[PDB]
Amino acid sequence: AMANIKIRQETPTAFYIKVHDTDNVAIIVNDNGLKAGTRFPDGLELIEHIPQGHKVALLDIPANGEIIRYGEVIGYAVRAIPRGSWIDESMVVLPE
Amino acid sequence: AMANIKIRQETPTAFYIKVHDTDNVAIIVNDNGLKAGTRFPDGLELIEHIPQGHKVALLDIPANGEIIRYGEVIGYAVRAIPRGSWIDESMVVLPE
């Protein structure tokens, strides 16, 4: 009986999507966004609400640190960005 | 970038545990039990609240049909048991 024990989770309805291995941000997926306290396996906990389709910081990003999505630098943090925070556009200087 | 896309689900907190392949019931896992409408990947939807540690019907079980856990017949349904229902003891005749 023990060879094939099965534990089945309740259908998942919230996710993040991380495109490239080097990325330090991911996209939030879930109807009206995800609330603070949302946990991900890996230790990630959202520290504020993040709208659907917006970016979450996968790690602490220091002020002026590279923000990386699809494996490219997409900008630099204006101020330090706590892991699990919403990456709002006002806090990103574009590369130029 | 596309070789290693990753979708990560919110940490699972509710489950059922099915011990043997032939079982038609499983144990519900989650603090104060699981409410009606709880969905599992496989099509299972709970039709009523089921306390933690109690059994859920994985399939429709006809009246007098075998109830199977750990791959043994553990009893027979007194009345037909809808898929996703709580297997309460009052509705099971023991094998003898």
Image (cartoon, coloured by chain):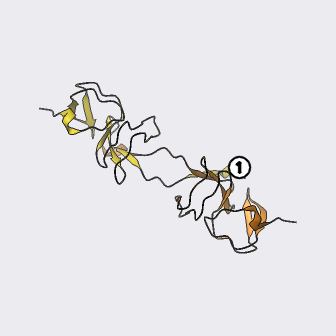
Chain colours: A orange, B yellow
Counting from the top left corner in percent of width and height, residue A7 is at 40, 47
Residue A41 place in picture, x, y as percent: 52, 58
* Residue B42 in the figure: left or right of residue B52: right
Q: In this view, does B95 lie above or below A25?
A: above
From what the image shows, is residue A54 above or below residue B72?
below
Q: Which residue lies furthest to the right in this view?
A: A96
Residue A91, relative to residue B32: is it above or below? below
From the viewer's perspective, tell me whether residue A11 is left or right of residue A30. Answer: left
Q: Is residue A21 visible from the viewing direction of this image? A: no
| Residue lying at 42% horizontally and 36% vertically, measured from the top left | B44
Residue A49: where, in percent of width, then height?
Answer: 60, 59
Chain letter belonging to callout 1 = B
**A37 or B70, which lies in front?**
A37
Q: Residues within 10 Å of mark 1 (few under 14, many from 20)?
A: few
- What residue sits 15% from the left and 32% below the top? B95
The answer to whether residue B78 is visible is yes
Check disc 1 and give the amino acid type.
Answer: Met
Residue at x 27%, y 37% (from the top left corner): B87
Residue reaching furthest top?
B63
The answer to whether B21 appears left or right of A53 in the picture is left
| SS label for mark 1 | helix
Q: Which residue lies furthest to the left in this view?
A: B96
| Residue picked out by circle 1 | B2
The spot of residue B32 in percent (x, y) is 34, 52
Q: Which of B22 and B36 is in front in this view?
A: B36
What quarter of the picture does the C terminus of chain B occupy?
top left
Q: How many marks?
A: 1
